[PDB]
Length: 135
Image (cartoon, rainbow, N blue to C red):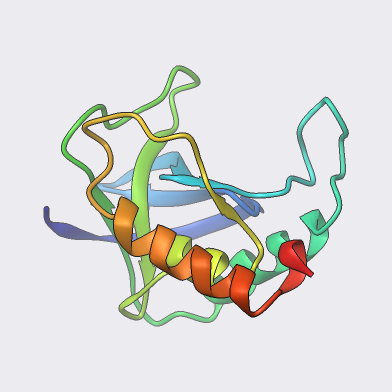
């Protein structure tokens, strides 16, 4: 896997950000995590949704460098969003959400599962610490 540079356009929700990538605006979905949404229809605003959304927004708006990392499989989902791991100054946004109890590891589809054990490791610690979703 390779990290590539990108520029923030807009944070949209806890699990989605719009980035300038290779000179094209693109919406990206964070790989491997299920994040409580402020969007969504079967609820609209979910519990911990505003908190997860603010977390992601702050992390990307305040970064000096954003990088995207695609996994080994499909790079876009059926809504046209990029499927990637997103880093803000070297720190993976997907893992940071999970470590804080603001996301769960999602149902995983091979072969987009390169960082699966790493996130599940962080999720086990957040539940042990009883943080946010786990409290």
